[PDB]
Image (cartoon, rainbow over all chains, first blue to last red; front, top):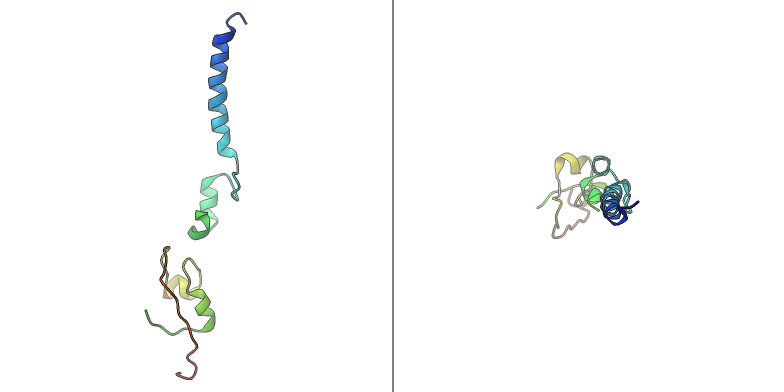
Amino acid sequence: SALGKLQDVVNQNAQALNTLVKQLSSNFGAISSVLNDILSRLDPPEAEV
Amino acid sequence: DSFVIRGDEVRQIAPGQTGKIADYNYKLPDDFTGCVIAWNSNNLD
């Protein structure tokens, strides 16, 4: 850990991208996170919400 | 638009609703429909 600051920069960027990708799995208050599934099993007027 | 339908079909004719009349007979668009006016016409029949 001699190169602490540079490794910290790399880790911070990896952390940001990783959490950004993790947000996709989050439900966000809808019936399901995966978008094809929410499209498939509801009518378009209801699925829109 | 003028047509004659039964009381249940009156419920059926709404935007985004699904029913035998709604699926095939008559479909409302997924957009505002101005108004829907329904009254029984048994005396006229």
